[PDB]
Image (cartoon, rainbow, N blue to C red; front, side, top):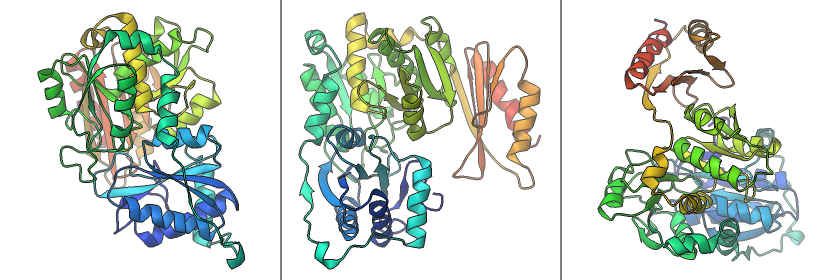
Length: 455
């Protein structure tokens, strides 16, 4: 996805592109990177190459003198939380995030609990290619991998430590949880149980085949669970992705809400819990401007940024922000941790919902309503994306609106906004735009499509 590393680690179809041989090499590199005698926690989500890959990684880390720990299956926020507060020097999670079932990959989390910074991906990448590995002598190759049984338990308690457990327990909520046949079923339901809810889970059994739906929660994949949400009259529903670092909700009406709608509501509650903290949150240009509208009437500035969760986690930390979030679910609550944490989100939601004494459906309605229209258009050869940018910019900019070119080109105007961004995976430019008036949005997309087409 680069030389190795993509947007969220190294990944590929298991036993084909992501082969045991590659992971074995990537492991000597990661191990050499952390150093001899470093304590590294290894965990995994539910995916297809699960066991095979954990054995390869462990074998790889021993060859380079790492003191290896096995944390079994768990949400990534959970594994990360473990390395963050349990003393580890870092960790490596076997996961392909949201990718379809045949994928799997390697995420590497640094000393702080967040995935390694990019400059570090390069160090590992260099080590991998130059093969400079701290391979150790036979006589010091005498260690067994140890077991780590505190990750889930430590995680849940950590999460529970930030919400009024009794207040919520009192509301005795009726919730539905869609862990997508994965690792999220080992913890979100546990947090629900502590907040005393009646719990219904769809796809709560572990199945690396993801038969019921794609692991990535989208209006399309949630289509059917949104149904059962309604048919079961639940007060709130929550869906996760493969390693549960994401959380998109479904209210009492049985309608799914997008990551930035709930990120905004959650970004709000975070200020209520910390008047002392710098009213200010971070979010990617992929997020609806609706966030500014709503957080504005609370003095919470929204710091726009590039697309990418790892980066956000760092920016939130680096600027001691209130919180951070992506439009795709995944919200960062600093007091807990800087990374996206689905269960953490589900818990905060039940709090916010509990203290407002309003239904999920109503709660969400308190937000600005915008209509989204998106599209993909191929990048014609002999046409540079920098030229498209230059154009739409000098045609849509105006002292009326405001432009953000930290990643592609985002334009924000009264009751409408858009983002034209170059894909890094496909030779395509994504065009998304929404407005309080569905027609000015559709129209917007059309105009943009033209310009992107080099007219």
